[PDB]
Length: 50
Length: 50
Image (cartoon, rainbow over the protein chains, first blue to last red):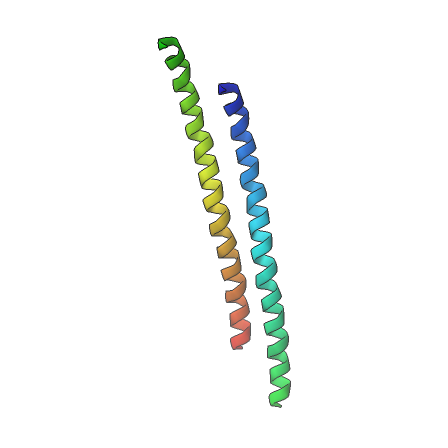
């Protein structure tokens, strides 16, 4: 079990990176989809006001 | 049982590291996913206000 835990620490160190990529990708993809829509709506609003 | 406890201390000393990696990786992955989204929303908000 001690040898399994030496190996398991490295697996947990890798899962911490896989979980950071999956979480940041999801959060960034949603936030950037809102930022693009709000910029399109904002640039459109400047012309509509004109 | 005394010989088993000498070996078991080393296993528990290793599990304390595995448990620190699993807990810190989970906490960091969530917090950084919020920090990235809140930065995208903040930089987007500066342009929307402009």
